[PDB]
Image (cartoon, rainbow, N blue to C red; front, side, top):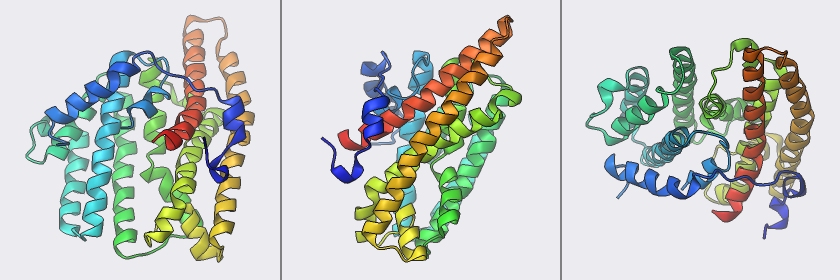
Length: 310
């Protein structure tokens, strides 16, 4: 049930889908939140196949943040095609402020900002302040990355290949989704653990696959819409690739993500085994790493099948 150019047999054979038991209540509860926040007149299935093991309240807050994220991206796109640079700048500034102090913005006149503030307020309630500050530091970067995308897209500038890859780690919010692994498994990871090279590399590859596979699926539509910002378009524009050639290159980069992930997933799980040193704290850290890496794995199949279902 998958067009041959988009089919990844290793995902189909070796990454069995998982579904969180709270999924049936997720979409309606998110709809109710969007309605209460006046953010509409779904990515919830995507999240339910990703953050396995999350407490119901954690998954619900992630789903609401994820849905808020979809509304912000629609607004961003509309400001882009209407060239509303003043409106975008003001939103960009309000989101930076609301991120650091959400409580002051819970009833802001801009419903997108008030909804962001409540979403982030709820995410800040699961782990210690040090995790909250990490999330904020990471999302400040996402906001500025969205600003560089506004710059490129309003001016019709196609970024270079590495320039796009570096930017897309930020607009896709790679490190936000990675941060959210930790409230899902109930444990803030020490820097020495989450900065372990196997943990970092596993987390990166999971996110690269998701962002690059999205670009692969959307490439034909986006070149026909004269878009910029897609890995295939940077390759066409800057490496003189034809469309078929760019589809083949993105596809190979996507396939290699998988097998590179399988190798580093072994290293991350060995590390998880090393953390279980016979102490209670070590067992806790080991289970958290193993749960987090398992969800890094779940991202692959959740994203793959989401594209073909939605």
